[PDB]
Amino acid sequence: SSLAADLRGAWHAQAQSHPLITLGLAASAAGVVLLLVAGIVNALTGENRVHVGYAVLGGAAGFAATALGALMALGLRAISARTQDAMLGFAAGMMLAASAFSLILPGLDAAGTIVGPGPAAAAVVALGLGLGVLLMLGLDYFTPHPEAARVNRVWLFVLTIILHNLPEGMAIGVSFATGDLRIGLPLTSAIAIQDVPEGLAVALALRAVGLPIGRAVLVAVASGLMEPLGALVGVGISSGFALAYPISMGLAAGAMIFVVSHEVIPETHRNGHETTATVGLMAGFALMMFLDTALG
Amino acid sequence: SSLAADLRGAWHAQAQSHPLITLGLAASAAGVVLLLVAGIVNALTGENRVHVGYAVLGGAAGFAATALGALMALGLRAISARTQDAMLGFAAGMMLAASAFSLILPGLDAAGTIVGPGPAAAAVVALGLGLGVLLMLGLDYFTPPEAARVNRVWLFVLTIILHNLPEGMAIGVSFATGDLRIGLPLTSAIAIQDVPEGLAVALALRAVGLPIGRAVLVAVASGLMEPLGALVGVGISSGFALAYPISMGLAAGAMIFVVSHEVIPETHRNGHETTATVGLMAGFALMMFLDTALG
Ligand SMILES: CCCCCCCC/C=C\CCCCCCCCOC(=O)[C@H](O)CO
Ligand SMILES: CCCCCCCC/C=C\CCCCCCCCOC(=O)[C@H](O)CO
Ligand SMILES: CCCCCCCC/C=C\CCCCCCCCOC(=O)[C@H](O)CO
Ligand SMILES: CCCCCCCC/C=C\CCCCCCCCOC(=O)[C@H](O)CO
Ligand SMILES: CCCCCCCC/C=C\CCCCCCCCOC(=O)[C@H](O)CO
Ligand SMILES: CCCCCCCC/C=C\CCCCCCCCOC(=O)[C@H](O)CO
Ligand SMILES: CCCCCCCC/C=C\CCCCCCCCOC(=O)[C@H](O)CO
Ligand SMILES: CCCCCCCC/C=C\CCCCCCCCOC(=O)[C@H](O)CO
């Protein structure tokens, strides 16, 4: 009846019930660890020369944006679901444009120069892109959605609340892996716009579980530490070999498209203000497209 | 009766009872926050071009060493206090030599080229060096019956997670120049330290009342402060030319305070005083030996 046994049993249960999601998670997990090892072994042997500095400031900004919203949960009055859906809807739009125009596109240009700009450029991004979708489909499924029992769920809840921002951080690290501000700033800022609404929501979600407002906020602030930590994971997976960057550019794109469509867009519609949320999605997408078009 | 109010009152209480420890902490905190902003503003305006990469892999090693020791708390049999005193005494010896020979020395050479190798070199490390002692004295002093017993398990786990941030900033400061002869000795010294305290942190949480697995899970997560702290360490070393030698001193003072006032008392508490002391000698001597070999 230890939560370790509870996790192993539930993980056994879902692996039996969803074998392809489970197999697709095993493969993606394997790739991430392999590109990470490769990127560490490359570093240990000299010769790496990645751009960690910009990724570290990028991850830190995200820490602050999460905290910012986390602290909005102590304010007086309230923020209606109506305003949150627009805030979350706008961010989801900038996040869609960013993984299209700041990660999938440059990742083709990346893989273009190594292996050829044809179907060979397209199939290297795809290896990442499908791998990122499968990665976050498995984490969605192998993550949770009566005194001793009720407590362990607060544990299983707080831990996926803490970790869930690691991918958003790894996308940040991958955009900045070449130190290119035109690749990085659009993505990093788009995740920072998203972090404010999710910071508030993460915090209020914890208060709903039963933590007093202050620990609930302190846990919400600690959630943003995964984006500095993830950015470190992102730079290392981009860097074992020449093909690791475009694969990773693809994998971050896949991870971020899955999170928006299958996780955040349902949050906007669940509150019921469907029209205002999707018009934001258009506004977020269009303006992000405009800014990448301007800076080129 | 909220835990926020309980912390605010106790911080008011300790600031009244220890005014110089309190002002000495206000001052040190101030410098670190200032050297960080300065170091970030430097990057945002271009011109920084430091390589965090070396500090990042160093911080990652520390994560693993803490995790390593944390997971030893699931083992069969047990590890005697006698063996733990030797492990911790040896590490404290390597940490003293390292902040002497890998942080204070190079920090003098640093301030040497900037302002001169006389008393001008010595007073720039010292500004930092006293600032590191003052920083870790204040953190020692300002960190710690149903509703009451729980808020201390909260305040306990919270300082348990945070306590490695300074050990992490020392790592970032050794590597702030990407010089492996400064960096490797220091970070390896803390990684040797990280294994024994990882075991202790895990067992200490289990003694508080967390089941063995969450106690181990919290212990593993404590090691994340050394990657994160190392980022803080790179930013304070880098606002201006004098920020590096100050920070070399500031980590040295912070690390000397932790060894002498925190790690050495732990080794004696279990009672095997002699073995801890010759270990500390062995750790110091070999570390000196390796710095002399590496030059
Ligand atoms: C738009 C396309 C939609 C298609 C979605 C399905 C994607 C497939 C998901 C995961 C496949 C992972 C690729 C490696 C498979 C090798 C399985 C080889 O077999 C194995 O390794 C098993 O252990 C066999 O038991
Ligand atoms: C930023 C997030 C990155 C985190 C990466 C780690 C998270 C999840 C870790 C592991 C997933 C393991 C799933 C086990 C499936 C085994 C059945 C099927 O096993 C298999 O079929 C094997 O392929 C054997 O051939
Ligand atoms: C509990 C709180 C823990 C805090 C967690 C977040 C840590 C991040 C905080 C500050 C990061 C500043 C380090 C970057 C300094 C060098 C800029 C890098 O710029 C560069 O040097 C580039 O190479 C330029 O080319
Ligand atoms: C308690 C720990 C500290 C937490 C505080 C977090 C500080 C927030 C840090 C940076 C905000 C802006 C970062 C932008 C990404 C890097 C752009 C770099 O861009 C540039 O280089 C210039 O635009 C031109 O060079
Ligand atoms: C390695 C290269 C891989 C090649 C491409 C494979 C990528 C897989 C692409 C898309 C899979 C995402 C759709 C997820 C379907 C199940 C979610 C649905 O979950 C649900 O919510 C239920 O249906 C109930 O509503
Ligand atoms: C909860 C788990 C989340 C993960 C927590 C973070 C701990 C692991 C952090 C980083 C692992 C990879 C280090 C960076 C690899 C890039 C080498 C650095 O690049 C370089 O080597 C430079 O170019 C010079 O050496
Ligand atoms: C890596 C760990 C670094 C963490 C640093 C942040 C933690 C420090 C937190 C709070 C500082 C304590 C303030 C004490 C007030 C004394 C009033 C006296 O105030 C004053 O009169 C003037 O400010 C003197 O300068
Ligand atoms: C051993 C731990 C290792 C490192 C831990 C670093 C994380 C930081 C841990 C605790 C934070 C201490 C800050 C307390 C501020 C007290 C000022 C309060 O003063 C006041 O509020 C009065 O107004 C003063 O007059």
Image (spheres, coloured by chain):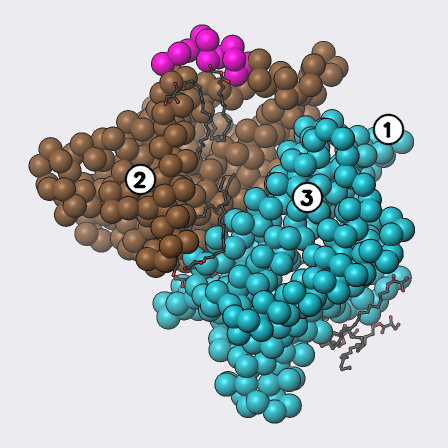
Chain colours: A cyan, B brown
Q: Which residue is mark 2?
A: B247
Q: Tell me the SS state at disc 3.
A: helix
Q: Amino acid at mark 2?
A: Ser
In the rendered structure, the residue with mark 3 lies on which chain? A
Q: Is mark 1 within 8 Å of ligand 6?
A: no
What label sits on residue A199 in the rendered view? 3
Query: Are callouts 1 and 3 both on one chain?
Result: yes
Q: Which residue is mark 1?
A: A147
Q: Nearer the viewer, residue A56 or B194?
A: A56
What label sits on residue B276 in the rendered view? none
Q: Tell me the SS state at disc 2.
A: helix
* Residue A174 in view in this figure: no
Q: Earlier in the sequence, mark 1 or mark 3?
A: 1
Image point (40%, 11%), residue name? B19
Q: Amino acid at mark 3?
A: Gly
Q: Give above or below for A138 relative to A213.
A: below
Image point (47%, 38%), residue name? B165
Query: Dominant secondary structure of the magenta stretch?
Result: helix
Q: Which residues are magenta?
A: B10-20
Numbered disc in front, either 1 or 3? 3
In this picture, residue B249 sits left or right of residue B215: left
